[PDB]
Image (cartoon, rainbow over all chains, first blue to last red; front, top):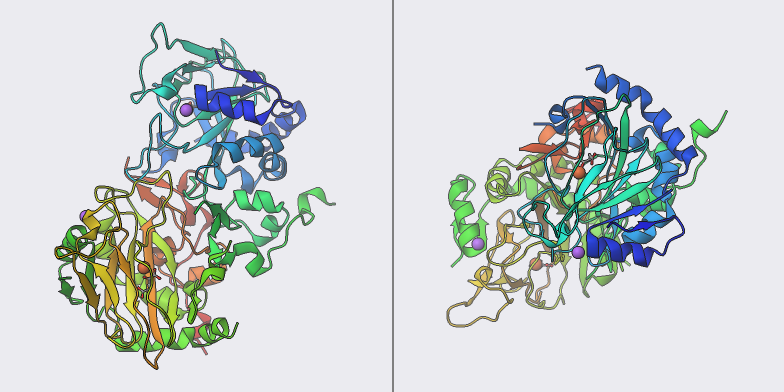
Amino acid sequence: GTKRFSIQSDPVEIHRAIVEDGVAIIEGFLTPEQVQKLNKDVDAPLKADREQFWLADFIPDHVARVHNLVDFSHCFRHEILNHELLHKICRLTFEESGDYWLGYGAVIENGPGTTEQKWHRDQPRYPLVKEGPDAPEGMLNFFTALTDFDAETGKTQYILGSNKRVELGEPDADHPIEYVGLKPGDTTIVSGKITHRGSDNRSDKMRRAMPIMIIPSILTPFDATCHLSRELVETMTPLAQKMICRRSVMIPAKTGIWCVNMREAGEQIGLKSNQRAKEDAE
Amino acid sequence: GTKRFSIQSDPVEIHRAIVEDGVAIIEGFLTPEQVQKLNKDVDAPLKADREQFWLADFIPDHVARVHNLVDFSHCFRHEILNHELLHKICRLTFEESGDYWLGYGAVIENGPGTTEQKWHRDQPRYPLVKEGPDAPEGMLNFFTALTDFDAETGKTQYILGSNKRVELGEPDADHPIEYVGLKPGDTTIVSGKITHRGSDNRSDKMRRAMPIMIIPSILTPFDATCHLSRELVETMTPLAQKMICRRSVMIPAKTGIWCVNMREAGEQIGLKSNQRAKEDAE
Ligand SMILES: O=C(O)CCC(=O)C(=O)O
Ligand SMILES: O=C(O)CCC(=O)C(=O)O
Ligand SMILES: [Fe+2]
Ligand SMILES: [Fe+2]
Ligand code: NA
Ligand code: NA
């Protein structure tokens, strides 16, 4: 089944598993303290969403979602966006296309009563973008548990082998379903090629996942970042600024795009980095 | 040869010419007054560039370039980005991919001594993006003359028929070179599929072109717009804001991406539009 790694594992082997299998698990990708911070950051927005074409209008019964985590989560913008293993894996995964950045960071909360989904792949279908077993990787979703994913709350089902297929496919003897159990802070790295579906939540608990969707930076993210203040952006590392569309990005020809004066976008406007954040201060 | 249209021509016929031929000309696409304003806006930056990997470091001998025209040209951000015929043509051209936005707006000034270029296509090659005679359109460059393009200053050469070829190709009897003459304000609409090269500038004059490069909004622009102030952005029309990555954009599934709270990016932050500009005021 799906290879399970730790935070100390070789990114080369994690990348190999993603290429071969379409999916890999990192146990303890986040620490329990990080999980705690992230849950506290999204408690109020999730409660507000729940208490209520745009994709906001297509959220399934009993599911609440909150997007644009950079806007309001200190942990997300400083810890998650600088996650060293995430970056080692993404650099290898997207090497053919060049740099990568954040397609979106969100939390999805499946409440009791959430129903099993249809088989799908995560990658949007665009006429201009190559897709399929032999295409370059178009996305990686570090699908991170913030609560337990078990038999009751729902384990995501992956059709092993489906990353090699053109059609979504059905499980057979040689492509059985794996139901992936996760402890909070474990992540399943989901390629755009692997067929999967979430399960029923038939427990009494909220089941929360934080997709960290990474895409090649030649493609537009789902979550906009253009409204973020220069103040907030300047508290971030240069790497994390690059993940939110505030720095130039490299393409193989490497040369830069997303530029100012045909040069690096941040440097040309004097963009600072690593400045102290108001929320860390008294 | 290349079909020549006017500002009153049917966009359906212009689009047909782009699909069939890979190139179309609109005479009087800009008015002489617009040409005058644009030239005055770029005079100082061009002089500064001339008086001197990133593409800034690969500009050919005797050529000066200035990018990011939205930042400093009132005419560009209010007149060009709202050009009604440009939009009718782009909506038809990019219908398979959804919405479109500004890949870059620049002025290229070929001084006396500028040499004929190598045959090329304008569209960057990315492993993930389909290219070729049968691929969806990946870019349209409204290559707009700001000075005369004639035998002396240099007419751009297009290999007629090359949009149907996989390789760049060479002119033959059935794919002859067309040298396109332009008066200031005439535009050649250049698809990403047509093989072409600029000519020598063997005159005593500066030869200026303003590429208005439009790309599907699923793709990242060459010119960043993330540093523009909310003040400046709020002076623009909602359409022009969309061209500079400040509004959500539609994809066929239509649904929106580049979102805030999975909804329209500007509306969610209360983005104003059509506000009076400081440079129009006393
Ligand atoms: O896997 C899940 O439980 C839901 C995440 C997912 O598959 C999706 O919503 O696209
Ligand atoms: O056509 C020209 O004269 C120069 C514009 C062009 O072809 C290019 O620089 O890519
Ligand atoms: Fe999924
Ligand atoms: Fe060109
Ligand atoms: Na693979
Ligand atoms: Na065509």
